[PDB]
Image (cartoon, rainbow over all chains, first blue to last red; front, side):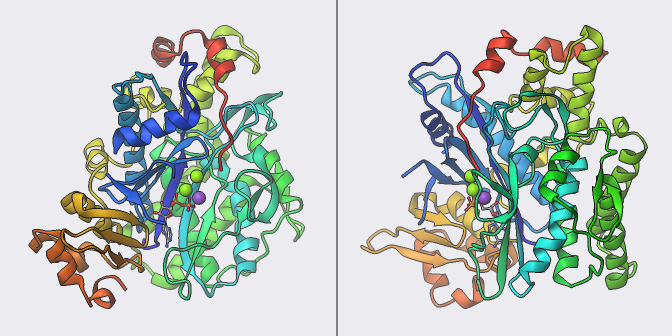
Length: 471
Length: 28
Ligand SMILES: Nc1ncnc2c1ncn2[C@@H]1O[C@H](COP(=O)(O)OP(=O)(O)O)[C@@H](O)[C@H]1O
Ligand SMILES: [K+]
Ligand SMILES: [Mg+2]
Ligand SMILES: [Mg+2]
């Protein structure tokens, strides 16, 4: 698999028993207590040596992965973000203020507020947006059957009793739009690629729940990428559009038995699982048609896992309790409901819903499941730890992160599309543009970075070579 | 359930106060 992608996750943040605290201050402590160099364009905003961004957004600490090229790397650097958040909070506890800061990789307080886990995908600019919209809406409406993180409470305000597949569904209100904080659209239309806008669209997806499960994050990014390849190539000839897709989004979420039927415009009546099976079958045909059996292993793995998950969801979803967040969480919830005869309104069930996402290794419920061997993993912890400080090798995040590690004292600022150097003696800053996501890689600049012992030597060697190393 | 005993061991104290106090600013 090769598609430039990334995940931005806003974390919930709680500072109990500190009347002097506010969410912006606590988010700043988290970002600042971890780190490094500033963001290039007054909130705390840091670029890390793994190429990630750590910053305060809307009174939430937010982690954005480096650009990666495949869904396994998306999982890996996204999981490293969880470790960075947990460590950041632990370091903030040693600041003079002494705050115990709790962080949650979820999307709602169950009281009407929501915050986002966004996926970004690089696409051909030429692909017509009307096709992007009409083929993605039904996919996004239904992919929560394996992407959902689970939620106790129905309706944005949480007043309805019961369990649902996703946290985000109740907050989406329209099909298409610019918004990210209110009246949220199934398809967000912002197109800000931080790359050659003549070549690339950046698809900014906002509808997904943050996932703890690595299998869920892998499927979320990997299946979406496969659907994007079909959309770009004009491969989908059928009409998957449904009547009232916003209503369908909510109704699919609110039926964890997975029997609710969408009403397709072409007359078909299909469950969300059934409609997902139609996308999967087209993806299989697409890959066979394009590559034969010359398919890369990861594409094959995504297709196989997508199919197995849908087959098991249709048979008995509880056999997925080691793979999907909403199933793993529901298994705990129903266990307590059976053991202690609890209605869905019980406060203990609300606590399980939230604490599932706590980043602490010793207290977060997903993390306890992993500790007891009750969750399947995709990557191992040693690789996650390495990904906290090393960038991916095959995107421009390589140059960004390695510059920060090796020449941090001489980096004035950095962003997705530039690194800005502050060289000794020069009374002027050197801005090195990194405009192509698939340049600035180890194959392009690794040897050069190895040889240079100073940022001055590096900027000298890069001078006039922008259209070699970076564009 | 062995696992429910593990979850019981780690759940936040004052569960009702904890849930009531978990109030977040809207994000994206
Ligand atoms: N050209 C691109 N194509 C696809 N994904 C990208 C591209 N550039 C950056 N990304 C990813 O998008 C995310 C940007 O995060 P952030 O700066 O928080 O976005 P926003 O401006 O939407 O808040 C990162 O995870 C990054 O890896
Ligand atoms: K975003
Ligand atoms: Mg962001
Ligand atoms: Mg944000």
